[PDB]
Image 1 (spheres, helix red, strand yellow):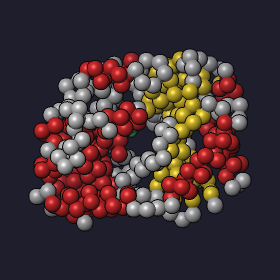
Image 2 (tube, rainbow, N blue to C red):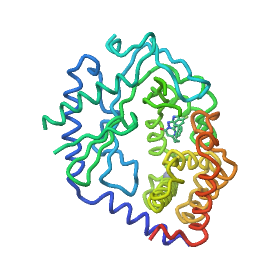
Image 3 (cartoon, rainbow, N blue to C red):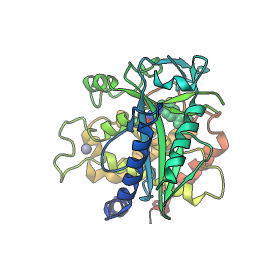
Length: 346
Ligand SMILES: CCCc1cc(=O)n2nc(NCc3ccc(-c4ccccc4)cc3F)nc2[nH]1
Ligand SMILES: [Zn+2]
């Protein structure tokens, strides 16, 4: 059918929409941090990645877990690709001079002061800070009991996208070549991240993702007739929720640890490329459309191939990233869900 899936999406929608003081608590903390960082020599160009009043919830089942990004513009950037990894880069070349080690911008130093400044502002305020191996997210704050906020520091570059993206973002037959060109004129972001430990940064395009999801049809009027939607966004929510529920179901074992929403999002956008017509996403076909997505993700697990949507030579499912045993384990869980009308969805 398609009836149970609607009930799941309705539950998720009402949980997200219900009245809550959490966004206001998060806002007060964030505004406090931004004011403090702006009067520091290294962070005076810092600001929120998106200045909307609705915060980012990466975990679709967790309305008390917030994700925020602080962006810092860096003029005249020089990038050097690290170890042929396509997605990881040294930063070379002003205010960030204090973090150089040679010609190379040190992420770990920059995070240390970012953390320290945030640490000394938290005490000035019911907020607590936790350091855990990371840096993207750089800092996790906890507000009262339930509310948590991940803060990521990102560099912004307004120069052309790196060569590794030249053949990515293959939306030309879905969103048009005109739109691909406008999107590629937008800035790109870099977040501190190791590939496996050097001073490397990873390309981040979460603003492009958000723009496409809000203007996602082949037809420009897609989903504007509010009673005859497409089901693209619902399919992506369902895929996100499937992985989150399986990860929770098996938090005691380790096999699903390396999977994240990047993997589900990526597979979904490949199915959007595969199926560019809005008629392939009719809301009546929610169940069949979700099954296309599930089926494609399962093909990717079995072939151990999932190309990054922006950098096609980066294989998210390579065996050095996620080993065979872990991919084979997620395959069997998903095919049990698929064959039993998704028990995690009730
Ligand atoms: C719209 C499709 C989804 C999407 C959103 C977004 O914001 N971005 N941002 C990049 N940047 C490039 C990039 C990012 C992460 C990883 C990665 C991830 C896990 C493990 C290892 C490596 C590999 C990469 F090549 N890719 C994406 N895809
Ligand atoms: Zn639509």
